[PDB]
Amino acid sequence: FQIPATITERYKVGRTIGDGNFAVVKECVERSTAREYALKIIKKSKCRGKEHMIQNEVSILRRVKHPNIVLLIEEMDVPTELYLVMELVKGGDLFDAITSTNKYTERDASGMLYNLASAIKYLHSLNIVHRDIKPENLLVYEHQDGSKSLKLGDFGLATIVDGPLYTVCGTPTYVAPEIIAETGYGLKVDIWAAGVITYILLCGFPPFRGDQEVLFDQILMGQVDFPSPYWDNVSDSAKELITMMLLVDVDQRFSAVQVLEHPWVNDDGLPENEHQLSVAGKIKKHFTAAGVSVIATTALDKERQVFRRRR
């Protein structure tokens, strides 16, 4: 690679930290601030013919400015490659946020859902559906006081909603019923995905586990079980919230605003903060490279995964 002068003048590019079929990722310290970023390099020879799937992801990253999102810091376009200076978040993903957390409680989970719901609210205000909201795409941003904030990344499946979408995209565990049914879907699939995550946050296992076709039936029926004894000492406010996020009826289902306005998220006193949640055990049973992985992927790496038995 012949890194342009524009980049090498204001950034010291280092070792390759990640690779992909369509992107290379290097260390990238901003010379003026000594702040560490990631330099994502895409060879335009691979993206030819499908410029739109790369260009549509970038034009979204260029717009979205929110603290709870992995941000595009800078773009440098040359005839042979596209350079993207990206935020490099090193606090691990969501599963690490739960494990590393000593004294893990409902208040921590509520705090993460606040960051997530806030990010989703921002995207939905711009009529952007992320469609790939999952624990692997939720990176942990650690502050100086020890507190943590989540940042949603990987906009490889993100798109502007102008009407109902029909492409069957996303990870089966987190995919909404309307995506599976192919009846048309929109923004609120992100809420469904967030509800699955919230469910996992409290107990460490998915609400819908199902064989593959059984999983899809579980999702389609949307009967959330809060089994004992795992949900015995979880607040009903939390279980109520998850119920509203995983409604098959899209109109009844909460919007991002309605999640944030829910007492368990809105009122920062409701979440239990003295009785712990023993979730660490279940996570391993069922489920800084985390930061690089989110950047190394592109839209062109995305594939369909959900396949019902044809009716």
Image (spheres, rainbow, N blue to C red):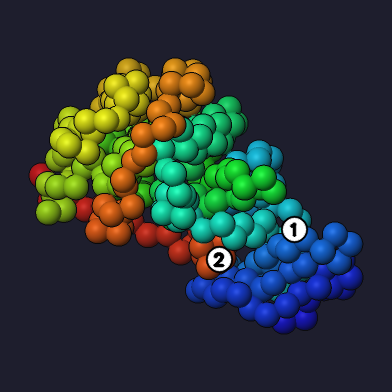
- Identify the residue at image location x=36%, y=49%: 169
Q: Where residue 276 sits in the image (x, y, percent)? A: 36, 39
For label 1, the residue is: 75
Mark 2: which secondary structure? Answer: loop
Q: Is residue 138 above or below residue 181?
A: below
Q: In the image, is 309 to the left or to the right of 230?
A: left
Q: Where residue 141 sits in the image (x, y, percent)? A: 60, 50
Q: In the image, is 39 to the left or to the right of 236?
A: right
For label 2, the residue is: 288
Mark earlier in primary sequence (2, 1) = 1
Q: Where residue 148 sits in the image (x, y, percent)? A: 58, 45
Residue positioned most to the front: 274
Q: Amino acid at mark 1?
A: Glu
Q: Is residue 128 above or below residue 260?
A: below
Q: Quadrant of the C terminus?
A: top left
Q: Which residue is nearer to you in this view: 10 or 57?
A: 10
Q: Quadrant of residue 225?
A: top left
Q: Is residue 15 above or below residue 276?
A: below
- Identify the residue at image location x=46%, y=55%: 100
Q: Where residue 230 sits in the image (x, y, percent)? A: 22, 38
- Identify the residue at image location x=55%, y=75%: 19
Q: In the image, is 235 to the left or to the right of 16?
A: left
